[PDB]
Amino acid sequence: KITPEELERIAGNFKNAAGEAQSQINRLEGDINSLEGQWAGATQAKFRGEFIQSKQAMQQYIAILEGISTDLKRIADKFRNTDNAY
Amino acid sequence: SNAMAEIKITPEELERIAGNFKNAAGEAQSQINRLEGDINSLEGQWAGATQAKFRGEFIQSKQAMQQYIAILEGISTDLKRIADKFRNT
Image 1: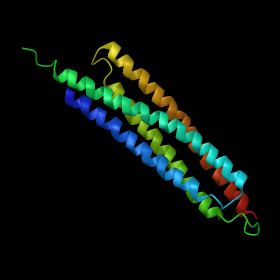
Image 2 (image 1 turned 90 degrees about the vertical axis):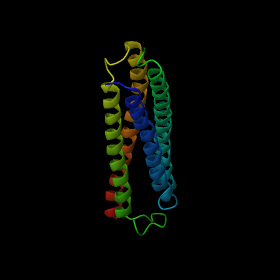
Image 3 (image 1 turned 135 degrees about the vertical axis):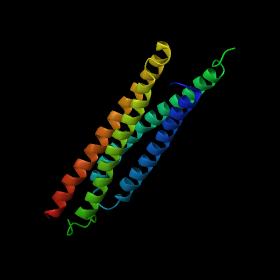
Image 4 (image 1 turned 120 degrees about the vertical axis):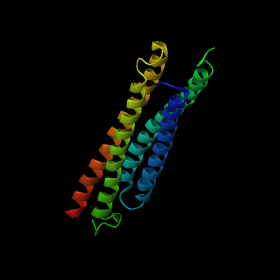
């Protein structure tokens, strides 16, 4: 059943997912960075460029998840103020 | 591989990093699936206009994730191809 508590739980799932996603992109960025100076510059340019594209996608993703979490919490508060009318 | 001055990275190191990208792609797919299940669990349990708002935003996130996953898998594949290339020289 949808309750304010359930909406808040799902909001937490979205917020936690955004954090995991940011951590993941941070770890992978470190790997690409570590290759700098370890092979040809043109090869590094390719992987840095592709990584930056992945980073742009993840920036978009995180922003959307954070918005969903915020909006779910807003609706949960509305539910908490609508529920149990008497 | 070894002889060329600017090739310093070993094939095994490239394969290690490739594994990180492959694993990240898998984790990312599992994540978007869990979150989709969450939005799905709300279907029909609140107003259609409310569900429509969240479904639309979620689908935007889902497309961003699809793009990301595709890029990560390409990076993993390419790193392994280059590791093979260096291992042969």
